[PDB]
Length: 106
Image 1 (cartoon, rainbow, N blue to C red):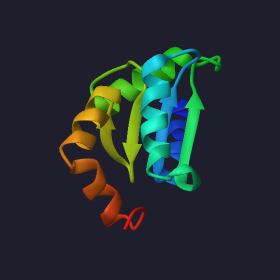
Image 2: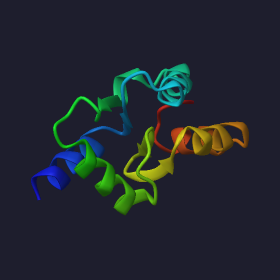
Image 3: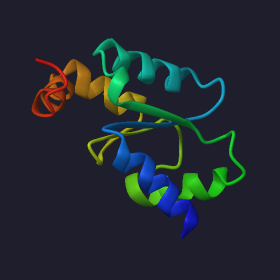
């Protein structure tokens, strides 16, 4: 209960929520792409490896998204997925569309 509530608060209180771990190249890439849209003000990155309940968090993220790996990316509570999912959305115009509907990019 506590772990799920804590994860939910991160997803619900931040338009862009990224779950990451230490020294994770695809986390770093995903975060950099998002900051490239000047989303910093509405982004939260949580390092779930630096947490006593990493496994519980990963299991919950899999319940929500289908995968336990990081990065795990949510935008306005919608599941984007991982860095590869973000790259596909970015290249195909879907990411910009998401952000426009949220007023985050013109």
